[PDB]
Image: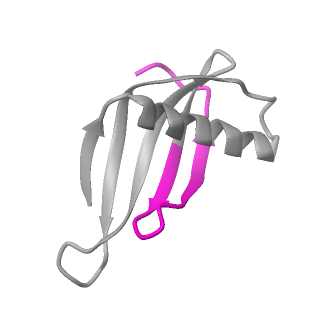
Amino acid sequence: GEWEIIDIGPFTQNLGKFAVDEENKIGQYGRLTFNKVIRPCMKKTIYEENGFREIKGYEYQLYVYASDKLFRADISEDYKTRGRKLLRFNGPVPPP
């Protein structure tokens, strides 16, 4: 697909908060308090198989501090309705 780096403004911090809220519903990790998203944040644009430059959706790979520990979260966002889903949430991981 196509990859780019995006910064850590409010849109990106809100993806982080989305990921921690979603993960807290599962309850496999102890309760997590969102702290902040840090660099780098990667954004992948996924295109329809057929067609020319038709966007299907995006995926965002984040480094997120929650309860003072660092995790990696992947989030999908559908292009048509902009609905979001947490794909994975792992860690703690080493700082980048």
Is residue 54 found inside the magenta-colored segment of the image? Answer: no
Q: Is residue 2 above or below residue 52?
A: above
Residue at 71% in and 24% down? 33
x, y percentage for residue 31? 80, 29
Q: Point out the image quarter for the C terminus.
A: top left
Is residue 95 found inside the magenta-colored segment of the image? Answer: yes
Using residue 23 as the reference point, say whether residue 17 is left or right of it: left
Residue lying farthest top? 68
Q: Is residue 55 above or below residue 16?
A: below
**Camera-nearest residue between 94 and 47:** 47
Residue lying farthest left? 52
x, y percentage for residue 39? 37, 25
Using residue 31 as the reference point, say whether residue 20 is left or right of it: left
Using residue 27 as the reference point, say whether residue 96 is left or right of it: left
**Camera-nearest residue between 61 and 80:** 80
Q: Point out the image quarter for the N terminus.
A: bottom left
Q: What range of the chain is rendered magenta? A: 74-96
Q: Is residue 58 above or below residue 14?
A: below
Q: Is residue 84 above or below residue 39?
A: below
Residue at 40% in and 65% down? 79
Using residue 1 as the reference point, say whether residue 94 is left or right of it: right
Residue at 52% in and 36% down? 14
Name which quarter of the figure residue 47 lies in. bottom left
The type of colouring in the image is one colour
x, y percentage for residue 66? 64, 23
x, y percentage for residue 61? 43, 42
Residue at 38% in and 28% down? 9
